[PDB]
Image (cartoon, coloured by chain):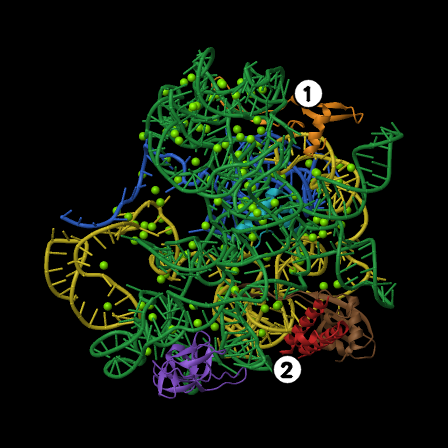
Chain colours: A red, B purple, C cyan, D orange, E brown, F yellow, G blue, H green
Amino acid sequence: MKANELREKSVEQLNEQLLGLLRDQFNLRMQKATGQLGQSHLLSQVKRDIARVKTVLNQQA
Amino acid sequence: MQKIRRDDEVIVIAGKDKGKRGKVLKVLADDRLVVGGVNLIKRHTKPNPMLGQQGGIVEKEAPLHVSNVAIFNTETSKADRVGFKVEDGKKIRVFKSTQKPVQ
Amino acid sequence: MKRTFQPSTLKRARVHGFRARMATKNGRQVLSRRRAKGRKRLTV
Amino acid sequence: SRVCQVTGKGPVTGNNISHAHNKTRRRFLPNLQHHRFWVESEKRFVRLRVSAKGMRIIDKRGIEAVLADLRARGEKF
Amino acid sequence: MNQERVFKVLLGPHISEKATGLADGKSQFVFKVATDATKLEIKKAVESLFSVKVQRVTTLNVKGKTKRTARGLGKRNDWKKAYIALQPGQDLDF
RNA sequence: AGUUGAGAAGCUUGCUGGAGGUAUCAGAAGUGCGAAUGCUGACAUGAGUAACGACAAUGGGUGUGAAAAACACCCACGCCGAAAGACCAAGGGUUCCUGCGCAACGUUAAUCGACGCAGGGUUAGUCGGUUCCUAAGGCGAGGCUGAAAAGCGUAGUCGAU
RNA sequence: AACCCACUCCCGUUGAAAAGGUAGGGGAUGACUUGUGGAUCGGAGUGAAAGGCUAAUCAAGCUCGGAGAUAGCUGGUUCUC
RNA sequence: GGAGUCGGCAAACAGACUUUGAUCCGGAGAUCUCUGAAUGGGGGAACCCACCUAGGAUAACCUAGGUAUCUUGUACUGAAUCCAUAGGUGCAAGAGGCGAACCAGGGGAACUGAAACAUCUAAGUACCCUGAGGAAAAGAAAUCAACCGAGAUUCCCUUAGUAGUGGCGAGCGAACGGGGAUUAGCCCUUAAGCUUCAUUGAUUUUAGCGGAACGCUCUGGAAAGUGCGGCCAUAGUGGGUGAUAGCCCCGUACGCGAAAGGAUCUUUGAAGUGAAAUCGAGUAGGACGGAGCACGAGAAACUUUGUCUGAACAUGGGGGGACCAUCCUCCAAGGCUAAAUACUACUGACUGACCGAUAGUGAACCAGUACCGUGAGGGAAAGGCGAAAAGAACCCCGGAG
Ligand SMILES: [Mg+2]
Ligand SMILES: [Mg+2]
Ligand SMILES: [Mg+2]
Ligand SMILES: [Mg+2]
Ligand SMILES: [Mg+2]
Ligand SMILES: [Mg+2]
Ligand SMILES: [Mg+2]
Ligand SMILES: [Mg+2]
Ligand SMILES: [Mg+2]
Ligand SMILES: [Mg+2]
Ligand SMILES: [Mg+2]
Ligand SMILES: [Mg+2]
Ligand SMILES: [Mg+2]
Ligand SMILES: [Mg+2]
Ligand SMILES: [Mg+2]
Ligand SMILES: [Mg+2]
Ligand SMILES: [Mg+2]
Ligand SMILES: [Mg+2]
Ligand SMILES: [Mg+2]
Ligand SMILES: [Mg+2]
Ligand SMILES: [Mg+2]
Ligand SMILES: [Mg+2]
Ligand SMILES: [Mg+2]
Ligand SMILES: [Mg+2]
Ligand SMILES: [Mg+2]
Ligand SMILES: [Mg+2]
Ligand SMILES: [Mg+2]
Ligand SMILES: [Mg+2]
Ligand SMILES: [Mg+2]
Ligand SMILES: [Mg+2]
Ligand SMILES: [Mg+2]
Ligand SMILES: [Mg+2]
Ligand SMILES: [Mg+2]
Ligand SMILES: [Mg+2]
Ligand SMILES: [Mg+2]
Ligand SMILES: [Mg+2]
Ligand SMILES: [Mg+2]
Ligand SMILES: [Mg+2]
Ligand SMILES: [Mg+2]
Ligand SMILES: [Mg+2]
Ligand SMILES: [Mg+2]
Ligand SMILES: [Mg+2]
Ligand SMILES: [Mg+2]
Ligand SMILES: [Mg+2]
Ligand SMILES: [Mg+2]
Ligand SMILES: [Mg+2]
Ligand SMILES: [Mg+2]
Ligand SMILES: [Mg+2]
Ligand SMILES: [Mg+2]
Ligand SMILES: [Mg+2]
Ligand SMILES: [Mg+2]
Ligand SMILES: [Mg+2]
Ligand SMILES: [Mg+2]
Ligand SMILES: [Mg+2]
Ligand SMILES: [Mg+2]
Ligand SMILES: [Mg+2]
Ligand SMILES: [Mg+2]
Ligand SMILES: [Mg+2]
Ligand SMILES: [Mg+2]
Ligand SMILES: [Mg+2]
Ligand SMILES: [Mg+2]
Ligand SMILES: [Mg+2]
Ligand SMILES: [Mg+2]
Ligand SMILES: [Mg+2]
Ligand SMILES: [Mg+2]
Ligand SMILES: [Mg+2]
Ligand SMILES: [Mg+2]
Ligand SMILES: [Mg+2]
Ligand SMILES: [Mg+2]
Ligand SMILES: [Mg+2]
Ligand SMILES: [Mg+2]
Ligand SMILES: [Mg+2]
Ligand SMILES: [Mg+2]
Ligand SMILES: [Mg+2]
Ligand SMILES: [Mg+2]
Ligand SMILES: [Mg+2]
Ligand SMILES: [Mg+2]
Ligand SMILES: [Mg+2]
Ligand SMILES: [Mg+2]
Ligand SMILES: [Mg+2]
Ligand SMILES: [Mg+2]
Ligand SMILES: [Mg+2]
Ligand SMILES: [Mg+2]
Ligand SMILES: [Mg+2]
Ligand SMILES: [Mg+2]
Ligand SMILES: [Mg+2]
Ligand SMILES: [Mg+2]
Ligand SMILES: [Mg+2]
Ligand SMILES: [Mg+2]
Ligand SMILES: [Mg+2]
Ligand SMILES: [Mg+2]
Ligand SMILES: [Mg+2]
Ligand SMILES: [Mg+2]
Ligand SMILES: [Mg+2]
Ligand SMILES: [Mg+2]
Ligand SMILES: [Mg+2]
Ligand SMILES: [Mg+2]
Ligand SMILES: [Mg+2]
Ligand SMILES: [Mg+2]
Ligand SMILES: [Mg+2]
Ligand SMILES: [Mg+2]
Ligand SMILES: [Mg+2]
Ligand SMILES: [Mg+2]
Ligand SMILES: [Mg+2]
Ligand SMILES: [Mg+2]
Ligand SMILES: [Mg+2]
Ligand SMILES: [Mg+2]
Ligand SMILES: [Mg+2]
Ligand SMILES: [Mg+2]
Ligand SMILES: [Mg+2]
Ligand SMILES: [Mg+2]
Ligand SMILES: [Mg+2]
Ligand SMILES: [Mg+2]
Ligand SMILES: [Mg+2]
Ligand SMILES: [Mg+2]
Ligand SMILES: [Mg+2]
Ligand SMILES: [Mg+2]
Ligand SMILES: [Mg+2]
Ligand SMILES: [Mg+2]
Ligand SMILES: [Mg+2]
Ligand SMILES: [Mg+2]
Ligand SMILES: [Mg+2]
Ligand SMILES: [Mg+2]
Ligand SMILES: [Mg+2]
Ligand SMILES: [Mg+2]
């Protein structure tokens, strides 16, 4: 999820993009603790997409 | 750029395998290369029953210094040096002897 | 036999603590002197 | 402190010398008293801590001129 | 609490023999929770995220273990534990 | 090891070692140790000698194990019992429990351990704090005092035993 | 008796202990003993007064500076002819 | 820029990233928990408890802003007391803390030397405290000279260990006059200069790019070494590559470079400041007690001031080492001013008749650490396999040691 397409969205659209990412991060942590997390690279990937949405959100001001 | 890239045809100068022709497989940090088919060793691997299993005697290539190989000029069949031709808009690598680009 | 060191965590902090040193300007000289030498603890 | 409030005199240091010419440190202090000065414009008494030399200056220049200087350098008189 | 706070308080299930025994005979589920979470926000997050009825939450702080190594003395992170009691009959699945 | 000078010393070689050395004549010195109850490290003598920390006390059987006086269980015997039994506070900080271990630690051995590795374990409206109140005392807006730093103190607000 | 103390003997003196132990001893409702918190300190404090005590240190604590104080005094001072 | 990458001790197992340009390097942004000047109130630093405004939820809150103290200016309000003052609230602007040294001030020892010791010395040193700056301070003659003249301040070399001073002991110690570094003055009938903006050009700094010329032979595990012949040079005693390399690699001489920040010098426009209003009065001079002048009361001039006094107005006043006369030379009690000078905690480059692990920093290594002490504080030991882990598969004794 590059920033260029994030800037193509509205403020209301970006908040639900943000909110749906936090749900995905929760599922990965729940799945990590139980033990059925095969792809461990997904944990850090979702963190930087959350940081990317918050950056573009702040740029909107 | 760097004069020796991955998957280049080279020839070995200096060392036990001086004169052998190979192809670059891996470029390491602190200017070392792994060239296919040269500088072979045998590592004796202890197969500990714990932590799964292992092997016996494995075969692999040991890295050698980057300045111990030379680009191979497949027109004169000799080793050569490379310079960087002035970029029209693109950097290219040329043979010093004949000024042809390397391919 | 009673020995000289009788521990007490409350009395230790009120005499040698960080806020006790910061109260007076002579205590603040101690802290800057320990920062200059590179002490890891700096206070007890 | 022991500082005159119109001239700025403060304590200064020096020596006592005996007959055998031994020296010990000493201080010289200004001769300062409390005095209420009548201010004609405001119809009130202003109380200052001044040296006897400061009262000589007030007599020469008046209290209005001196009080202006004290306000000029911001002194809580 | 805002909608971002619900996703950050629960860290995951706690797996142990004590935790397993409580899930069967008492309908009591052990979770790892954020170290600044409180009983009230733990209760709401479980209800929202798992869609169940929770009756009571008890919480305890756990000190990290200190391990001596060749290069000094290091210690592990402190964490917080929650015992979560559900309604008489219902389960907490994922 | 041999050999050469009056001496400090020089030279030539066998073995070891595996990458540096410096003829000659000049220049410059952190330039030469046996002592300083010298300083640092290593190792002797004493000597396989003293000691092994309350004179409550131990004896068999069985098991495990490479190995049992010391570990576990059983049958007996001894000791404390206004403690050598339980519980709060202070102080300590994982020493608590369970698997796997025995090099070092344990004044002996150790299969055992407050020892090593890895997991687990502490659940409060009523218990103890926090929150409310103040004592001795501390700090202290303004203030008064003082070469400066600062001292004392009012309103106030901290401080449990 | 507990508790506070420390009169005698012996042991111990490289100690179980840088001041103890066993056996005897004194006070034990008071000028008592004790927990927690607080105040006073270096020519200064405190002292029912021994120049005692102020972190195993006291006829002037410890620490860092002046500082490599000064030492007509001890000790040592390294290859050859 | 141009192909590898997910930092190190410190390896393995995994999961991935990508020439549609990754990792990496530089400029500008965003986020930036708690403590700490710590600043909403407390507190045993990294903790506890709040209030107000706006917005959002319905339960037991969320989000974003505010709330220390002092100084300066401003608005309102207002005691004894009529007036108006002290005081009380609200706004703005500033400060506060840290830092090795250098600078200007306030306070200020002793050991020691004098072969004892008081005056004296050490020394206005150590130390403590307060302010400022990139430098600071001082600076434009009420100055020296000597009847000839010089021309603000600061720093260096001499005069000279001289004249002086000194229980005339131990010791302290100038000036005049010369040679240099730097070059500069301008105002109170309102100036040079300096700040902050806005503009005119140039130069640098924060990253990078290109960068010449070697083959054969012997020994050897391995040539850069032997022998033989070449080539490059504004690049020839650099580093390291399996032993000693101008021509193998990275470099070097020499040439190019910057979307965007920083800084310096430069034009010309504004605002401010300089600034004290009008040439200087409780001032010059004097008496007593001290300090400073190399000068310790000495024939002791000159500066300064704790106490007490106290002028003249250019036909007037200061100085020329007691004091008088005559001459000479300056115009104090109001300001601003660069350069030459001091220092380096910090950053880069280069260099060394410096050290090479008991040396050099206490510290080559996870060091102000371990350890010691209640604390302030004190304070260690400890580097090297090999070119390359190729770091010893497998068998046997032994407790699966
Ligand atoms: Mg500090
Ligand atoms: Mg004296
Ligand atoms: Mg708890
Ligand atoms: Mg609790
Ligand atoms: Mg030899
Ligand atoms: Mg060498
Ligand atoms: Mg030589
Ligand atoms: Mg030496
Ligand atoms: Mg030496
Ligand atoms: Mg020597
Ligand atoms: Mg000797
Ligand atoms: Mg010796
Ligand atoms: Mg000798
Ligand atoms: Mg001896
Ligand atoms: Mg000695
Ligand atoms: Mg010796
Ligand atoms: Mg020694
Ligand atoms: Mg022996
Ligand atoms: Mg014997
Ligand atoms: Mg015997
Ligand atoms: Mg014996
Ligand atoms: Mg014994
Ligand atoms: Mg038995
Ligand atoms: Mg026994
Ligand atoms: Mg009894
Ligand atoms: Mg018992
Ligand atoms: Mg008991
Ligand atoms: Mg505790
Ligand atoms: Mg302990
Ligand atoms: Mg442990
Ligand atoms: Mg345990
Ligand atoms: Mg146990
Ligand atoms: Mg076991
Ligand atoms: Mg054994
Ligand atoms: Mg042992
Ligand atoms: Mg043993
Ligand atoms: Mg024992
Ligand atoms: Mg254990
Ligand atoms: Mg009070
Ligand atoms: Mg006070
Ligand atoms: Mg105050
Ligand atoms: Mg209170
Ligand atoms: Mg209480
Ligand atoms: Mg007694
Ligand atoms: Mg007896
Ligand atoms: Mg007794
Ligand atoms: Mg009694
Ligand atoms: Mg009574
Ligand atoms: Mg009584
Ligand atoms: Mg009595
Ligand atoms: Mg009491
Ligand atoms: Mg106390
Ligand atoms: Mg005190
Ligand atoms: Mg003293
Ligand atoms: Mg006394
Ligand atoms: Mg007495
Ligand atoms: Mg006394
Ligand atoms: Mg006596
Ligand atoms: Mg102690
Ligand atoms: Mg002590
Ligand atoms: Mg003592
Ligand atoms: Mg004395
Ligand atoms: Mg001295
Ligand atoms: Mg000495
Ligand atoms: Mg002596
Ligand atoms: Mg003699
Ligand atoms: Mg002797
Ligand atoms: Mg000696
Ligand atoms: Mg704060
Ligand atoms: Mg505060
Ligand atoms: Mg504020
Ligand atoms: Mg606060
Ligand atoms: Mg007012
Ligand atoms: Mg400041
Ligand atoms: Mg500084
Ligand atoms: Mg001064
Ligand atoms: Mg000064
Ligand atoms: Mg002075
Ligand atoms: Mg003296
Ligand atoms: Mg003397
Ligand atoms: Mg003498
Ligand atoms: Mg004497
Ligand atoms: Mg004397
Ligand atoms: Mg005398
Ligand atoms: Mg003196
Ligand atoms: Mg001074
Ligand atoms: Mg400053
Ligand atoms: Mg300035
Ligand atoms: Mg500054
Ligand atoms: Mg500045
Ligand atoms: Mg300058
Ligand atoms: Mg100046
Ligand atoms: Mg000036
Ligand atoms: Mg003339
Ligand atoms: Mg001039
Ligand atoms: Mg004399
Ligand atoms: Mg002169
Ligand atoms: Mg001159
Ligand atoms: Mg750059
Ligand atoms: Mg290049
Ligand atoms: Mg090149
Ligand atoms: Mg270049
Ligand atoms: Mg070289
Ligand atoms: Mg070698
Ligand atoms: Mg080379
Ligand atoms: Mg070659
Ligand atoms: Mg004038
Ligand atoms: Mg005068
Ligand atoms: Mg006088
Ligand atoms: Mg005099
Ligand atoms: Mg005399
Ligand atoms: Mg005169
Ligand atoms: Mg006068
Ligand atoms: Mg005069
Ligand atoms: Mg005249
Ligand atoms: Mg004369
Ligand atoms: Mg003169
Ligand atoms: Mg002037
Ligand atoms: Mg200077
Ligand atoms: Mg410099
Ligand atoms: Mg060595
Ligand atoms: Mg060292
Ligand atoms: Mg050392
Ligand atoms: Mg300690
Ligand atoms: Mg300690």
Q: Position of residue H109 (x, y in %)?
A: 49, 31
Find residue H388 and report its image quarter. bottom left
Which quarter of the figure is the C terminus of chain A placed in?
A: bottom right
**Is residue E36 placed above or below C1 in the rendered structure?**
below
- Ligand 31 within 8 angstroms of badge 2 C-beta: no
Residue G1 in percent (x, y) is at 68, 46
Residue located 43% across and 82% down the image: B34
Looking at the image, can residue C29 be seen? yes
Chain at tag 1: D
Q: Which residue is mark 2?
A: A38
Please state if H344 lies on the left or on the right of H197 as rendered. Answer: left
Separation (CA) of disc 2 from disc 1? 98 Å
Figure quadrant, ligand 21: bottom left
**Residue marked by disc 1:** D60
Residue A53: name its quadrant.
Answer: bottom right
- Does mark 1 have its CB less than 8 Å from ligand 113? no
